[PDB]
Amino acid sequence: LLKLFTTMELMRWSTLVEDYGVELRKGSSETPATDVFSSTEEGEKRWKDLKNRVVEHNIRIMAKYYTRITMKRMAQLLDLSVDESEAFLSNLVVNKTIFAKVDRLAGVINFQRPKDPNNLLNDWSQKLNSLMSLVNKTTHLIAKEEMIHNLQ
Amino acid sequence: VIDAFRLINANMMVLGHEPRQTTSNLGHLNKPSIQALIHGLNRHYYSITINYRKNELEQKMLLNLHKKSWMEGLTLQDYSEHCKHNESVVKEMLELAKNYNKAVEEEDKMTPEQLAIKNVGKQDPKRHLEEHVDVLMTSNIVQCLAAMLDTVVFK
Image (cartoon, rainbow over all chains, first blue to last red; front, top):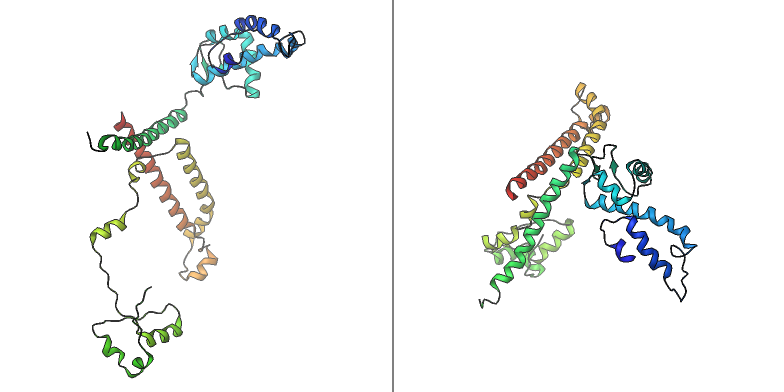
């Protein structure tokens, strides 16, 4: 249960519920089946929340890692329809769980800010500066490796 | 501020013997701290000449600063930062501008104390507005010039 969420990979509720259903509910604590908070009967009240959490997490990882994905691919993972996802998207962004913009076409999800001149500008400076720091550092290591004891 | 003394007695100064002994000197006199120091100096042997043994190899060592100038000449910052600088200066320039109108209309006065009160001559809008255009121009040129240079060369 810990290992799946920690590794950022795309998943879906449909598989997640069935599997964990057998593990968590069965799990011997001190010794009994009971542990609650998404395991047993009482645990079911908390479990409902777990579904919502999978869908906030799927949209988050895809947002961070990718910059564009289609809305049809996104829905399959979340286990929503487009009309259902769209409602959910309006409230998520307001709390600031994620930043994402979805359309009605289901052509695309822009997980970046729209292509305005400032983002392009910003990246272009950062790319330049990193190279210059790296070329300096490598020359210092290289100098020892070359000369050495002067046995070669 | 360095001085040299061999140090010889008071009488030698008084007689006027002490300049006969110094020959092969030029001498000099400076005053870090008033008449009391001058008197102390005269009693001693006053300033006997200091020459320096120096040359270009030693001179080159002292010259240095940073080889790190190599990385720095090329470096330019994030574009958001370029914008911060430009904004801060234009905003600043607005404040001083209102005095500037008066400055050009008047300033018949050439007497520094009177001018200061009259057309806000002290805290002058001319000095500062010029100073401001000049930082903004130079800053924008070096940042812009570097970004472009790096682009062509690395790829």
